[PDB]
Image (cartoon, coloured by chain):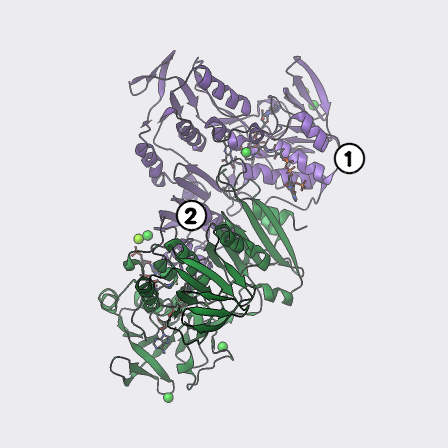
Chain colours: A purple, B green
Amino acid sequence: PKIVVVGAVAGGATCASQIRRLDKESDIIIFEKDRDMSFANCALPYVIGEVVEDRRYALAYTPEKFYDRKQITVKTYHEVIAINDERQTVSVLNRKTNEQFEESYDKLILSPGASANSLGFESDITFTLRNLEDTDAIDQFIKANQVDKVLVVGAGYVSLEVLENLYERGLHPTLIHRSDKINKLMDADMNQPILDELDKREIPYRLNEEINAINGNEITFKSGKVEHYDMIIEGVGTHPNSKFIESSNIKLDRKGFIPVNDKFETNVPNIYAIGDIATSHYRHVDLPASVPLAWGAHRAASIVAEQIAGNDTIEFKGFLGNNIVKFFDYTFASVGVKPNELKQFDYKMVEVTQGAHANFYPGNSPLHLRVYYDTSNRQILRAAAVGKEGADKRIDVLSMAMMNQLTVDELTEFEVAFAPPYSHPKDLINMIGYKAK
Amino acid sequence: PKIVVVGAVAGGATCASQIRRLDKESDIIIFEKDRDMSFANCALPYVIGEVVEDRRYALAYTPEKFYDRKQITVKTYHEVIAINDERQTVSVLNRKTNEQFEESYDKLILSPGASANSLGFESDITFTLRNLEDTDAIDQFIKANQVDKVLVVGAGYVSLEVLENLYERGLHPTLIHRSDKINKLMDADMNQPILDELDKREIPYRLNEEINAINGNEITFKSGKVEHYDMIIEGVGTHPNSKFIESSNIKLDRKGFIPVNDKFETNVPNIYAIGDIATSHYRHVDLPASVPLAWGAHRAASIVAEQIAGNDTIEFKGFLGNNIVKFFDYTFASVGVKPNELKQFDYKMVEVTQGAHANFYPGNSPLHLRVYYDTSNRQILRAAAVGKEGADKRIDVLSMAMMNQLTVDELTEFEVAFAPPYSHPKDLINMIGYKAK
Ligand SMILES: Cc1cc2nc3c(=O)[nH]c(=O)nc-3n(C[C@H](O)[C@H](O)[C@H](O)COP(=O)(O)OP(=O)(O)OC[C@H]3O[C@@H](n4cnc5c(N)ncnc54)[C@H](O)[C@@H]3O)c2cc1C
Ligand SMILES: Cc1cc2nc3c(=O)[nH]c(=O)nc-3n(C[C@H](O)[C@H](O)[C@H](O)COP(=O)(O)OP(=O)(O)OC[C@H]3O[C@@H](n4cnc5c(N)ncnc54)[C@H](O)[C@@H]3O)c2cc1C
Ligand SMILES: *SCCNC(=O)CCNC(=O)[C@H](O)C(C)(C)COP(=O)(O)OP(=O)(O)OC[C@H]1O[C@@H](n2cnc3c(N)ncnc32)[C@H](O)[C@@H]1OP(=O)(O)O
Ligand SMILES: *SCCNC(=O)CCNC(=O)[C@H](O)C(C)(C)COP(=O)(O)OP(=O)(O)OC[C@H]1O[C@@H](n2cnc3c(N)ncnc32)[C@H](O)[C@@H]1OP(=O)(O)O
Ligand SMILES: [Cl-]
Ligand SMILES: [Cl-]
Ligand SMILES: [Cl-]
Ligand SMILES: [Cl-]
Ligand SMILES: [Cl-]
Ligand SMILES: [Cl-]
Ligand SMILES: [Mg+2]
Ligand SMILES: [Mg+2]
């Protein structure tokens, strides 16, 4: 079948590649509105920090290389502006020439992702971070203006990674956020180490703070404070790239995302949606779920490839919402329903704080593990872990437990790999099980 | 009920403690033949390495403290010499007075563990490592003799830990082993980094090598080599501490271990056996298993506590055999049936070697993950991982998968916690699943 893909990055390029693995005959074309395909989204903060300096890590392919390797046509600077689903074409604007044209399809795969929100100020010193064009612009502005003082707005995982990287680059960032709800995927009372790490390094922060006005480099804040900054990086949320979809017969929810079934099919025949744009359900509970992260983009890409060119019995089983971020010496990871969703259940919480490994063993650090379970069936609803060591390990194990419908009580039976550098004869996970009841 | 426990360490002290949690009324007495209760068996190599300086780390309790906190009576230097099972008493030798007496019980819990094997040479320079007395003796001998050159006999995981610690303490060890099967719980080909690490630090080793004769500090070997050594640490296996049990009605296997049911009951009413002395079965396959490690001692301790004083529907579900060792920069972890047990199945092997985390993120290293599955039912039989980073995480996840008899194919569905320092959007675990078709 002739396959058209919208968006040439985490969902879209991956999906096209997976289809080509299975099907060497079909024509495949990807439209991408911006300059680059296959940029490494998650690498971008580290490019800014000069931690990742090799351009070959910042993006995997140019369209020419992608074609030479996979015989997939990718048209960059081509923006899909409408889906004409009744005639099975999309309308595409060639942004170089400013001319539009129709492209026909047998199958259409939508992976347009999300765009960064803006505070809307008229400021030449303000930047958002979503792609490699943005990353290049920030790097160039830093060099062109000998940037020293940077204001980082927003305290989600992206902003936090950007702040750490600016600091490691030798710059002097200040963090602000409109509320005290930093790193919102993590339990609110488990995020203190973020603030501790800022304090330890004398990196200023102000919560419940906002930009009030901008006059050149002079920034006036909600608090009344007035400061001079060389640069501003705004991390104030994202919005779905779905305006171009609205006129079509594809069903969008009220927030602008596309609900899909377990085959990642939209309501319209022959049209799939994957990545940040798509909404589905949790695997472990009967609730809607949207998890705009790389795992889901890649898993959906594989499932859609099977649907189109492989084993079409392969279907999604839902999200668990596993997520993680590093901030300086600490790891913050969680899985399951969001804190705000716990209220839809009768639940209990159990927690343990213990060394990540043998107490007598050096380099030890306190790991805090928390587990919420449903009182009606003893099933695990949510888990969260924060510490310098071992948090990723405990959360991945719990993700696998939830995949298997394990009860909190069965955690006593988890057989951990124990030697002094790694865990305890009764691991934190076991202790959750013992402490439950 | 009046409770008597034999052995006051990983299984015994833990079980007594767990019973007290549930039952504050019953009299509990533990007999321990040696000087110390509750010593940290797994810390001992690190005490030798002076990595653990604070001897407070090597001993968790004295009998006086145990009685103060838990009202449990522990008698050290008291060796149980016979079980008079029909009258429900044990015969106990007070090793300080050399007088024996009988102690009655309503319930008897055997956790006598295992003793170190010896090569049987008449040598004052040779030591084995099993308890804190042994650790003290080794440390004292090193100081008294200004030991430099040390012969480490045996290449099992504990001997390897002893070798590393001697090296880091500043001594010069040589490793020998009677066969080429070093670190035998791991796949033989995946053990190469042990030899690499030895070579990198110019630590000599000889496999298929044995001591032929000892004449003072002059050691003659099977190879014909003659070398001078200041000290020898023999790690040549262990044997069950069951000689005192043979006259009783308790059934022992041909190797001297005690088969138990899933309640850790022996064949004799009111007598339980836990820890290294006990044999059981695998959880995921129908085969006998013996896994003489700390997790199993602690888990059995809790189950027996519930049987005696708690919820008597709580039973063991079998072992998976999860195990792990660190050797210098590398981690070696495995779970499931042993290499020699694979032949009892029709099986296939899948493997991947990939960076532990995102390739662009600094400090990466290649992680080798291998999974064996049963061709009759796709179920995971065994998994092994070796690398500088991430091996413990992958093997713990697969232990949780096997606990639920998960299939190899379902690994594609595992939802990893992904950010660049930790994994990949398609994790090594996912890749095993994708590669299994
Ligand atoms: C700085 C940063 C750090 C991140 N770190 C992590 C992390 O550590 N872990 C994690 O799991 N996730 C992380 N993410 C999120 C992750 O990158 C996303 O979940 C993933 O990119 C989603 O894939 P996608 O295909 O839906 O969107 P994208 O990868 O953003 O690609 C969508 C593409 O569609 C194009 N497009 C949109 N509309 C049109 C149109 N009408 N016509 C043509 N092209 C169009 C866009 O220009 C864009 O290039 C990070 C994201 C950012 C920006
Ligand atoms: C140096 C070393 C390192 C180790 N490292 C690890 C590791 O990294 N990971 C892991 O999982 N396991 C490790 N182990 C193994 C672990 O310690 C055992 O599996 C665990 O101790 C078993 O518990 P147990 O109660 O059966 O035996 P033990 O803990 O050895 O206790 C048994 C006790 O019973 C006493 N006893 C025996 N007979 C009598 C009698 N007739 N009367 C009175 N008392 C008696 C003994 O003197 C002994 O103190 C290590 C063991 C050693 C020696
Ligand atoms: S934000 C976090 C993640 N970042 C992003 O995703 C950024 C944008 N990513 C993309 O654009 C695509 O993911 C790109 C990078 C374009 C994918 O193309 P690649 O050529 O780089 O990677 P491929 O998936 O095409 O294949 C690479 C190798 O990995 C193994 N492999 C992939 N898929 C499978 C499956 N389904 N089954 C078994 N193995 C698979 C392969 O061994 C493969 O190399 P081979 O040539 O097949 O040996
Ligand atoms: S070689 C590797 C293993 N070898 C060893 O274990 C060495 C010898 N070990 C022992 O002697 C015992 O294991 C000792 C050290 C005496 C400890 O016994 P317990 O395993 O029963 O644990 P503690 O009584 O010392 O309590 C410590 C903390 O763990 C909590 N806890 C234990 N058991 C439970 C149960 N069943 N349910 C809920 N919580 C439990 C304790 O309450 C305690 O928490 P703290 O806040 O640290 O007090
Ligand atoms: Cl990436
Ligand atoms: Cl139309
Ligand atoms: Cl705690
Ligand atoms: Cl220990
Ligand atoms: Cl008798
Ligand atoms: Cl039996
Ligand atoms: Mg129209
Ligand atoms: Mg504590």
The answer to whether the residue bearing label 2 lies less than 8 angstroms from the nearest atom of ligand 7 is no
Residue linked to disc 1: A25
Q: Is residue B6 left or right of residue A72?
A: left
Q: CA distance from mark 1 to mark 2?
A: 46 Å
The image quadrant of residue A245 is top right
Image depth: mark 1 or mark 2 in front? 2
- Quadrant containing the C terminus of chain A in the rendered view: bottom left
Tell me if residue A178 comes above or below residue B421 in the rendering: above
The amino acid beneath tag 1 is Glu
Looking at the image, the residue that sits furthest to the right is: A25
Is residue A402 or residue B115 the one in the foreground? B115
Q: Where does residue B313 sit, x and y in percent of width and height?
A: 43, 68
Is residue A259 or residue B298 the one in the foreground? B298
Q: Which mark is residue A390?
A: 2
Q: Residue at x 39, y 67 (%)?
A: B129
User: Alpha-carbon neighbours of circle 2 within 10 Å: few (<14), some, or many (≥20)?
Assistant: many
Q: Is residue A356 visible?
A: yes
Tell me if residue B304 comes above or below residue A303 in the rendering: below
Mark 1 — on which chain does it sit? A
Q: Earlier in the sequence, mark 1 or mark 2?
A: 1
Q: Residue at x 59, y 50 (%)?
A: B411
The image quadrant of residue A177 is top left
